[PDB]
Image: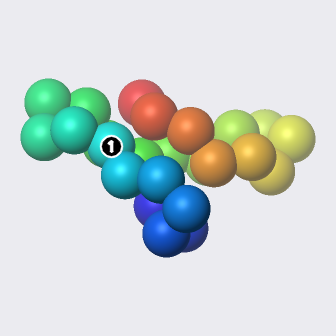
């Protein structure tokens, strides 16, 4: 993640092709 947001335990933080933070 980056810090602005936080993902759950069942999910993980992943980056997108465009360069945006998301949840995978």
Q: Is residue 9 left or right of residue 19?
A: left
Question: Element type at marker 1?
Answer: loop
Identified at 86% across, 41% down, the residue is 18
How far across and how far down the image is residue 21, in percent? 63, 48
- Looking at this view, name the residue that lies furthest to the bottom: 3
- Crowding at dot 1, Cα within 10 Å, few <14 / some 14-19 / many 20+, comes out as few
- Looking at this view, name the residue that lies furthest to the right: 18
Q: Is residue 22 left or right of residue 18?
A: left
Residue of label 1:
7
- Looking at this view, name the residue that lies furthest to the left: 9
Identified at 80% across, 50% down, the residue is 19
How far across and how far down the image is residue 12, in percent? 31, 42
The C terminus: image quadrant: top left
Q: Is residue 10 above or below residue 4?
A: above
Identified at 78% across, 39% down, the residue is 17
- Of residues 1 and 16, the one nearer the viewer is 1
| Count of numbered circles on the image | 1
How far across and how far down the image is residue 6, in percent? 37, 52
């Amino acid at each position: 993640c980056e810090g602005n947001f936080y993902c759950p335990a069942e999910k993980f933080c992943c980056k997108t092709r465009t360069g945006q933070w998301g949840c995978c």
